[PDB]
Length: 228
Length: 228
Image 1 (cartoon, chains in turn green, blue):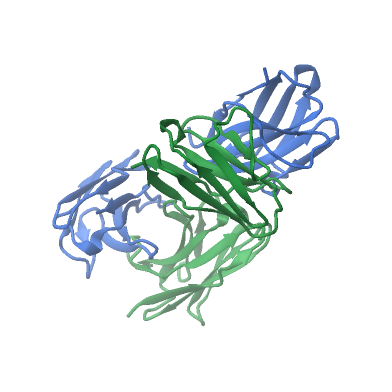
Image 2: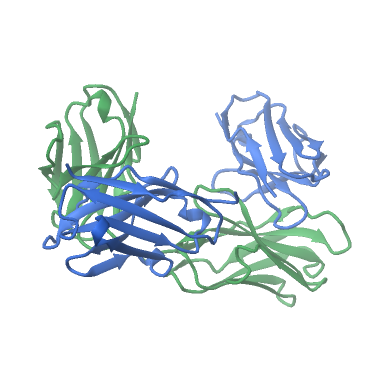
């Protein structure tokens, strides 16, 4: 059985470096070309680079030619991807995939590894639920959980599709001017709540909590309130 | 009377530059902090940069600290965001937003502009349709893949079950790879390629990718999600 196993991923700060490895077994490692392919969260597949040890060739996606380095060690049956100057945009699952033999003329990816997770991040606000369905007149409750104590330094925003966000609640529980009284906020420390006591047709939108204490003033991922 | 209006957005190629402008009116432009907030397509809000002219301080999200520059034209009551070395992931709606006056520690965005659209893209191409479809067990599924250039049966099709690694289904446009069930069929040539699943099975619910086999960068299609 032909098999590929990636490893070496992890959580790294931006500007850092990572070296992914791709170990092969069950075939002649030297003759085939090895590819790297990555997939950012919620995005499609993107080819990164290739190397064929026997031909002595390496080819990169021009998007990564300067920052990434592909290499092999035939004695270990292992290919490598050295990634430098890591950006948050490099957060993705990284796969190695086997291509064609040097004697053959068709280059499809027939054997894939399981993938290795790479996350480029500075490490705060977790919003729940991600989406919900309700009816007019319902009472809706949305929660926002912070990784650190925020006292009451939390804001809530409403954003209808194709529109700009609007301030709803400032300082955890205070109603911004012009905001209807059916909106209520509460909580302090790390758990915060937005409540819509009587849902109206104009309330179906996405709601965001926001840490206002220091930069980068993280927003929660949002809660989408849809019509049932 | 407080108002913000963004302008300067547009469609540019990777590596180019844009300069967004935020025209403010109805308040003391000098005393308040102006912020830039962006929203990548179908995603949450992310704070970009801030400037307080009165305090003489500007602060950046570290993601943009050396490609983006924020500034103000006091005579125009206008803030600017110069964006250099634009990447595809900088595609977003860009808002300017007022926060607290120079003496405020809290950081709530009480006034927002309408936002301006920034698209960073090439304007070689592989377009799939549909992007997503819902079907039932036993149904027939037909996925279409369009190349913006001629490929001469150099197209592969892949299946990617959720969270798992992609698996080769069809190579060279129509040939069924070994071990692949025969209910998968591929065909087409030139710029037009089609994948058909005759009898949809419960394990076939996944995302399906076509791929340009030659030459580099071995571009994948956006993928087609097949739900139930």
